Length: 57
Image (tube, rainbow, N blue to C red; front, side, top):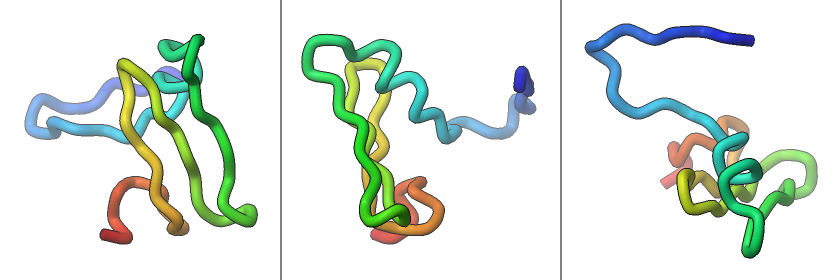
C-alpha cells in the first residue's frame, strides 16, 4: 500500500526494490520462513531475523 513517510525519517525498509530493480543478479529468498534475503542495485536488505531490517546485527 502507498504510504508516504515524514521528512525526519531517512532510511526505510523496501525489499521490493531489490527484486524489482535487480533483474540480472536479483536475490530473493527466505531463511526458514523467518529471515529475508534481498540483494539488488537499488536495494540492500538481507538478514536472518524476524524484522529483516538489518536489526539482527
